[PDB]
Image (cartoon, rainbow, N blue to C red; front, side, top):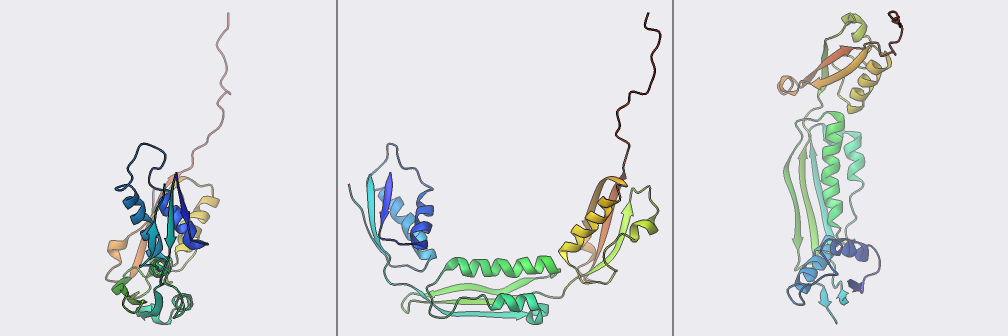
Length: 245
């Protein structure tokens, strides 16, 4: 069993997380082992801005860790190109960046990149790409600098929805589609299309597949909705009996 001394809060939690990965109570080393522990502690600390800790062990095994000098945010440079430049959700995201002079948290940078992609997926920026995405650490300055250059491209629009397998005439299905052809894509519209088809009770199964290989030149996304007619599921005990004797 191993116990960490010298950390207060999120540092301490992240480091305990990192440590609760390797085995403890067992038959194990003393120097090769505590050099795995040493590595794991340093990994946790780096993620939270501490690249130059001091760590010292004892005897259960207790590790005296002093975080040391932090790396501070020196800049959070992000360029947005394509629709994202003027897109209200991407602009809101820029305002979440950490302030200059705060202690580096690497997770902020990674979560920011993931948020760029998450918005792109929800709003149909399917040509989304990074031409730059670096976290640069100048340890001699104890400063960290983001460098993201992100191009969302254009928002895709919905195309025509083709239905297959239906017992229902097409004009009645089309009436259920919750967008017009030519509307900008939103992921929630696929959920609503599912919900509307579902609410009719017409089908046993519905599979709605965006046809993306039809969309890269046009930025218009057709959908194909393959359905199966609902069949009656009741307890068959109407049929009478032969003579019992």
